[PDB]
Amino acid sequence: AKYTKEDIFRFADEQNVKFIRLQFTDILGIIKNVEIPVSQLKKALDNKIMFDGSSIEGFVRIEESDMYLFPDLDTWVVFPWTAEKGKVARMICDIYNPDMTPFAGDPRANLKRVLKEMEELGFTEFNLGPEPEFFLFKLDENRRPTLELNDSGGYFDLAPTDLGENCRRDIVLELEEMGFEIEASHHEVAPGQHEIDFKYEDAITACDSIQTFKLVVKTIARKHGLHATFMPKPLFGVNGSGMHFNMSLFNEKGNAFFDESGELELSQTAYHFLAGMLKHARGYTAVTNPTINSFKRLVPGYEAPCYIAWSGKNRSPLVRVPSSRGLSTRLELRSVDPSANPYLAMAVLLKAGLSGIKDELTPPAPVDRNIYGMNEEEREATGIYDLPESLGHALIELEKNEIIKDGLGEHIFEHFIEAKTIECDMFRTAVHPWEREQYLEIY
Amino acid sequence: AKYTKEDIFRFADEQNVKFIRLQFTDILGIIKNVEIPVSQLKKALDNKIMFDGSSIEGFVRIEESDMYLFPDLDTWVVFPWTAEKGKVARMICDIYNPDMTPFAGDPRANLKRVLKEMEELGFTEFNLGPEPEFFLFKLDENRRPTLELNDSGGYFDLAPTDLGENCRRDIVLELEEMGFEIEASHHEVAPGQHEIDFKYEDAITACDSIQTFKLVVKTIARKHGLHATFMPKPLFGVNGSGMHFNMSLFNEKGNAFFDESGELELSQTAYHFLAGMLKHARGYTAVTNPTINSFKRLVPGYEAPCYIAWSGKNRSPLVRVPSSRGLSTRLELRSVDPSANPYLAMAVLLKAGLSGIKDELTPPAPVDRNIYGMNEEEREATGIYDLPESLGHALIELEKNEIIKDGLGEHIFEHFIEAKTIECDMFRTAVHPWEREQYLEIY
Amino acid sequence: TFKLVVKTIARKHGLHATFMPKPLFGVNGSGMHFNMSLFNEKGNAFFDESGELELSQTAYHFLAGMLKHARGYTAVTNPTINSFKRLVPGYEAPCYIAWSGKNRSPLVRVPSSRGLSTRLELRSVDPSANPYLAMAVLLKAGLSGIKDELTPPAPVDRNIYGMNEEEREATGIYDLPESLGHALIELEKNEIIKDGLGEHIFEHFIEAKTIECDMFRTAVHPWEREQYLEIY
Amino acid sequence: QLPRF
Amino acid sequence: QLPRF
Amino acid sequence: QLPRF
Ligand SMILES: NC(=O)CC[C@H](N)C(=O)O
Ligand SMILES: NC(=O)CC[C@H](N)C(=O)O
Ligand SMILES: NC(=O)CC[C@H](N)C(=O)O
Ligand SMILES: [Mg+2]
Ligand SMILES: [Mg+2]
Ligand SMILES: [Mg+2]
Ligand SMILES: [Mg+2]
Ligand SMILES: [Mg+2]
């Protein structure tokens, strides 16, 4: 408990806020919110605000359903770009049924349920550190995004330099001012691609920070006449954007993944987690990569993962074990992209790891022989398997796997499949200019 | 034997031709040709012209291979648009190995081999009538095709009218002048879409007429400042272009598909042919629809077939039996599109029908209950199955089926598979503007 | 005459006809493959129905001579700097000294036609070469091979591009010169090609080509600026 | 239900 | 082999 | 001698 009701009232009085954005996240990952004046703040703190819960279902909503808006006090953040006519503050809210029960269709509530299951098994917390990457594009005269990148930088290069501009520096400075724990910030391989690293927090706090980071980055980029995009693969032939997740599991003693007497200084819990993560990777690939464009990133030659394998040092492994040990022991999943919903991805990953721990599965031997060297047939003999190549195949794999369904819940699973099958069909029937440039004069 | 060598020499002398285009068709269906002066014509008639046979393989060619250019005398056609500085004539040529053996990789030779097998089984000829449909687009200032149709017509409508233009009328008039047997011509459902029907000839003659028709239509449309395209689905939300094939099998007595004493006035041979065509439809769907744009046409609601079923009167059946009987008895396959190679499609269809006749398979009962009414699950209980939804699935079905491989030959099968897999990989990794319009701003 | 007439007619129709070996990067180059046959009183000297591959011993000696001195006359057959931009892998231009009846870009190819049409095809020649000098050096190499009765190496059909340079240098496969300077050095080393060119032509050709190489070497190209002006 | 299409 | 690509 | 240069 970081803040209380009285603290929130005092903050609202002293910082002179007149608007509060009670925000939440739908199934598709879009940040939505209800806007209330400061005069209603007390009612908001009484968990008495009603709204339409069907919006959580996204565009596949059918029937209006009334739901409560239980806010979280610890998520109180005051925005700085609010001029003087009253400031704006936000609090991430939980969704509750009218019968005082958390909504099963809320991704945050689902993540809380999965964390409760993990605590039941014996662990304390699930620390996560994300590595989101984003692209910056120049705006047009009509304030519309173009295809021109802001700079032709390189990997870890000092490309933006000093003397103005350097949108990454301004973004990180305002994030630090807003109260974000930023570890580092650097230029990525692709031109105009930047990465900012976070500190390791709890699962829920990390997801909330991810959403707030996306919002703040987009707003600040729009301030400086730029468009910040988190599309997995905005351009062809260039490196994509990833959101590598470094996860660690903790218990009463400390880090559960660390064991000085184990092989690679890894505990049996870490190996069981690896086995669970690798066994069901084909299952949750759809959740971790939910857009059609996502699977355009999962292609060989751009450091994105393409095969289900783990290693300590390899060219684009699905799961990577960083060399750091002790309390910093962690497992990195590299298949996640910034377009994914953080809550759903964390829920499915935690469910897979928990299932692996419960079943005590033995992970396959790590591969370090450049699996890209052989053909598909030459590596299918071993345990190396391909990730789904399209969203439709990933949706089929979801519909087959049961543990991921249990980790998502029936409501979320049904609405996710419905929305994504529509997206697949919409993309399948469309006629793209690629076809009108390959078969127009030819045929 | 319609023409002899002396006839060809007399024609060349009297019509004053100075150029002869010895033409052929590659695996991909592109019309290719070697151009020789009239002074070499005698050598051309001696089957002594050498050329690079690897061009038949298309872009996937590796090693240069020398091959002969056996021409066909009956295909002598003199083009009318040649001004006065010498005329241009063409003859479709067969490809022969240097050891005086027909090339196995030539689609025409493969079709001849399949026809030889059919004659061995006891039949005489395989009459075919195609129904090609094409779109007309207006050219730009730089003589480049645009997306604007030439007219907003309708199905069987008198849209182009009189008083100039009416490119369909000019095309059919020049085709009649060139020596084409045109049955009828009309406006199709889509605006700017036109169909011209042919008379029923032999398989080889029908395929040659199809290729010549494509060439002549494109040239004449270019003459009047228009672009004629045979792309299966140039535009979204509009009717596609098809090349329905009406096939009939003949014997010494007459039409083998006609029997006054049989059900529906159809012989047992016709039913065996139907069973063979329906059994392997999932197999040769790749050959009949060889482009990515093709499977954009195979969508419900635009009269294109989507399910493996046959009927005498139904909304978009895969195989349709026209009401005409007697010597006009025929089976119509509607899944073929103008982009397909006529020789390969005829070869695979003949192989499927011949296999059905040899195995004496019983065809499924015709469906007339509007299969579109039920869902996929409600119709999968019966014999109704879906056609492949993408070119990759069709390629997999090709790689599984053996009879279609036998009907294509090892050389053609391998090169077709290689080219189509390259095409699928090229399309899969591309980033289309659809993806940017759907995710650049949202994410 | 063909070059002159083609250029004139292309200029007539508002076009420019060029015989540059490689006008554009990443696109196929232009070649001038030579199909040569040697005749005697009886008939074609390269044809023998009783020989292996229906080839006479004269044809094999000619092949051995052509392959032995290929590194020597590569300069004469490819006399421009742009020429060696064409001799790169992946565009069907030859890059290794080998012969075959059917292979992806061999240096010397034997067409399947026989009888009076028996011939050997050299594919390293480009349209920029002087036809007289190229024919002189090729004839000298073939004649030397016939006189010495050299045995040609076995043909290669295993896609030599599959292996690395080291894995194929163990066998008789060798690389053609990669630049005009190396080709000029190879010319200055070889003596039979000098005899086939004559002292006057050899000296003047060497002088002109060395001047051309020096002129190209000291130039600063926009590629260099695009690669280093901003980085450094 | 489906305003995307 | 691969002019398309 | 050297018009090119
Ligand atoms: N250097 C890196 O590891 C970047 C990886 C790449 N940007 C991705 O999205 O996976
Ligand atoms: N009216 C029709 O039958 C046209 C059919 C449609 N044009 C097709 O391509 O199948
Ligand atoms: N198809 C071919 O053989 C062309 C060869 C290539 N143009 C060259 O210059 O060698
Ligand atoms: Mg990174
Ligand atoms: Mg990482
Ligand atoms: Mg029609
Ligand atoms: Mg029809
Ligand atoms: Mg040649």
Image: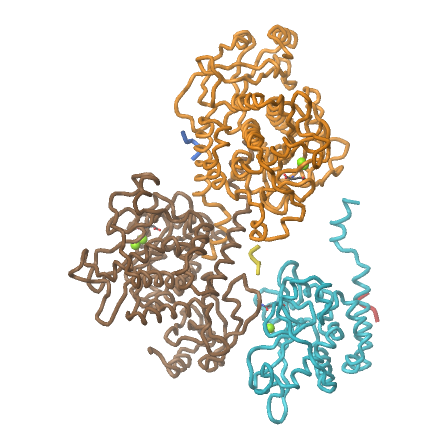
Chain colours: A orange, B brown, C cyan, D blue, E yellow, F red
Which of the 4 image quarters holds residue C187? Answer: bottom right
Q: Is residue B9 visible?
A: yes
Judged left or right of residue A439, residue A386 is right
Of all residues, the one furthest to the right in this rendering is: F1
Circle count: 0
Location of residue B246 in the rendering, given as x and y in whole percent from the top left corner: 30, 59
Which of the 4 image quarters holds residue A227? Answer: top right
Which of the 4 image quarters holds residue A386? Answer: top right
Judged left or right of residue A343, residue C143 is right
Judged left or right of residue B138, residue B194 is left
- In the depicted structure, whether residue A406 falls above or below residue B337: above
Residue at x 50% of width, y 25% of height: A26
Of all residues, the one furthest to the bottom in this rendering is: C41
Residue at x 48% of width, y 42% of height: A393
Q: Is residue A142 visible?
A: no
- In the depicted structure, whether residue B347 falls above or below residue B19: above
Location of residue A84 in the rendering, given as x and y in whole percent from the top left corner: 64, 13
Location of residue A326 in the rendering, given as x and y in whole percent from the top left corner: 73, 28
Judged left or right of residue A335, residue C136 is right
Query: For this rendering, which residue is in front, B70 or B235?
Result: B70
- In the depicted structure, whether residue A173 falls above or below residue A338: above
Quadrant for the N terminus of chain A, please. Answer: top right
Query: For this rendering, which residue is in front, A255 or C2?
Result: A255
Location of residue B94 in the rendering, given as x and y in whole percent from the top left corner: 44, 73
Quadrant for the C terminus of chain A, please. Answer: bottom left
